[PDB]
Amino acid sequence: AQAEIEQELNSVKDALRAQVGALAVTGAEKILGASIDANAHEQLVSKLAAE
Amino acid sequence: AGQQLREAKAQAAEIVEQAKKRANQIVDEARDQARTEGERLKAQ
């Protein structure tokens, strides 16, 4: 009657979090798939060669 | 003397059995009220 009310309340936040996280990953994929071109490899392949 | 002792002892057993019978009513009525209020809060 009190702990179970908090049990449902936090479970709803997690159900939303599971969808928002998927959307945030999809957003990052769409952004990078347009923001990356030949000007990025001279800043990434060059970085890996030091790692 | 023996007859009244057997009668008193028989009534003593009945007095204690009625107390046990009463205890179950006190406990189960508290369970139904507490569970009903829990559902009242859960729906809200």
Image (cartoon, rainbow, N blue to C red):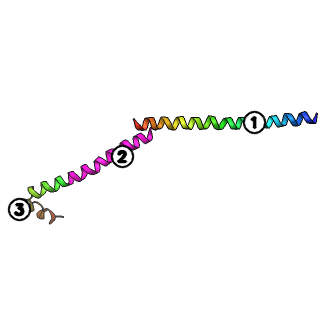
**Any mark on residue A11, and which?**
2
Asked whether, in this view, residue B35 is left or right of residue A13, the answer is: right
Give the residue type at disc 1: Val
* Residue type of the residue flagged with mark 3: Ala
Q: Secondary structure at mark 3?
A: helix
Which residue is outermost to the left?
A38
What is the span of residues highlighted in magenta in the rendered image?
Answer: A1-25
* Residues flagged by tags 3 and 2 on a common chain: yes
Q: CA distance from mark 1 to mark 3?
A: 93 Å
Find out whether residue A6 is within the magenta segment: yes
Whether residue B27 sits left or right of residue A28 in the image: it is: right
Mark number, residue B16: 1
**Are both tags, 1 and 2, on one chain?**
no
Check disc 3: other Cα within 10 Å, few if <14, some if 14-19, many if 20+. Answer: few
Determine whether the residue tagged by mark 2 lies in a helix, strand or loop: helix
In this rendering, the label closer to the viewer, 1 or 2: 1
The C terminus of chain A appears in which quarter of the rendering? bottom left
Residue A34: horizontal and vertical position, in percent? 9, 56
Chain letter, disc 2 residue: A
In this view, the residue in front, A41 or B30, is B30
- The secondary structure making up most of the magenta span is helix
Dot 2, how many residues are within 10 Å of its Cα: few (below 14), some (14-19), or many (20+)?
Answer: few
Which chain letter matches label 1?
B
